[PDB]
Amino acid sequence: GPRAGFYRQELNKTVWEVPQRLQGLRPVGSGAYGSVCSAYDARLRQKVAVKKLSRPFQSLIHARRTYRELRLLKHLKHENVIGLLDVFTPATSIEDFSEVYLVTTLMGADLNNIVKSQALSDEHVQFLVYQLLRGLKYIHSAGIIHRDLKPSNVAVNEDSELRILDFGLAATRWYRAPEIMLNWMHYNQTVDIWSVGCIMAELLQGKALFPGSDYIDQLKRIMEVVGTPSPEVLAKISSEHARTYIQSLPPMPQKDLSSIFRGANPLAIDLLGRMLVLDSDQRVSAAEALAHAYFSQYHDPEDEPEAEPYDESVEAKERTLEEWKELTYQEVLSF
Ligand SMILES: CC(C)N1CCC(c2cc(-c3ccc(F)cc3Cl)c3c(c2)N(c2c(Cl)cccc2Cl)C(=O)NC3)CC1
Ligand code: NA
């Protein structure tokens, strides 16, 4: 195990090489969860989660994406966002720098786990969804869009503390905004509010709101609740080419969400109604949603901070693979 004070083992067909401080590595699952282990960090003296990045410098865009992930994790430090406790590489020089390891808080569960193992009370949904929006307010205010928010990217520990995992870095399409589905090139932060809506719907009902079996079925299920858009709304939520997928559907009125969410807190229904809207910019913002009466138990404007804009200047400039690597290497070494 080349580097001093580091040891090697095989976990899910692949070699993990970690410092002696990291003990009892246990894979979370097989496949898409094959890059993450639970561990005990003997230096920090606590249980941790460790993520081995797949192939960080395989191409230009992967090198670029690796850098960005590191950057966002530092810039977006917040109570409801996952933050780095450690970062390392088995490399001793930039010449053998090919792997990056990220060490965070061990949360232990995601929102899927929460929905599966337990029926959720309305008061419990208020708390969970409050935190997710509070994390998202911060993310958005830095000028970052998640773009793929769903239950498996939202971590919750046994004290019901919630942290957002990842920022759309790189799957189910049940939580993706229609404008993303329809390849609208000019989407913004509001796409995540659609996802929050679907997530909140699922916490309340214990089941997915729009579980499409395929692309066309996904759009169908969606329109069958929210109604088909006017041409004017359709013009601002899709690529020209993707319009046919909505135009050739039968015209449908919006359903009454009181009939979909029968028995729910009328406040939840109201709010869901301001999130699950085709006209994207009519969607309530994360900051605005926090002020909604539904979260009136937990809302604290003084304690729902905004971020400084995320600085894009380094990534605005074109660099070689070998340069993104050197930038990432220094970023790792500086932790
Ligand atoms: C399939 C895709 C969508 N993805 C789902 C999320 C997974 C995932 C990633 C990360 C993560 C994120 C950023 C980072 F820098 C380092 C790490 Cl380790 C964590 C977790 C899970 N969990 C976790 C949960 Cl939430 C449930 C069970 C077991 C565990 Cl370990 C934590 O507790 N801590 C961090 C990775 C794969
Ligand atoms: Na606080």
Image (tube, rainbow, N blue to C red):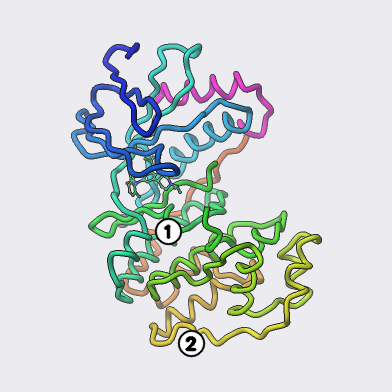
Does the segment drawn in magenta span residue 144? no
Q: Position of residue 183 (x, y in %)?
A: 70, 57
Callout 1 environment at 10 Å: few (<14), some (14 to 19), or many (20+)? Answer: many
Residue name at image x 38 percent, y 83 percent: 265
| 236 w.r.t. 163: above or below | below
Does the segment drawn in magenta span residue 334? yes
Which label belongs to residue 258? Answer: 2
Q: Position of residue 93 (x, y in %)?
A: 45, 11
Q: CA distance from mark 1 to mark 2?
A: 24 Å
Quadrant housing the N terminus: top left
Callout 2 environment at 10 Å: few (<14), some (14 to 19), or many (20+)? Answer: some
| 327 w.r.t. 140: above or below | above
| 205 w.r.t. 51: above or below | below
Disc 1 marks a residue whose amino acid type is: Pro
In this rendering, position of residue 50 left or right of residue 240: left
Disc 2 marks a residue whose amino acid type is: Ser
Marks 1 and 2 close (CB-CB < 8 Å): no
Quarter of image, res 205: bottom left
Pick whichever of labels 1 and 2 is earlier in the sequence.
Answer: 1
The residue that disc 1 covers is 151
Residue name at image x 39 percent, y 83 percent: 264
Q: Residue furthest front?
A: 13
Quarter of image, res 300: bottom left
Mark 2: which secondary structure? helix
Q: Position of residue 268 (x, y in %)?
A: 43, 78
Q: Foreground residue, 211 or 253?
A: 211
Q: Which residues are magenta?
A: 314-335
Residue name at image x 28 percent, y 68 percent: 118
- Ligand number 2: quarter of image: bottom left
Q: Is mark 2 within 8 Å of ligand 1?
A: no
Residue name at image x 57 percent, y 65 percent: 213
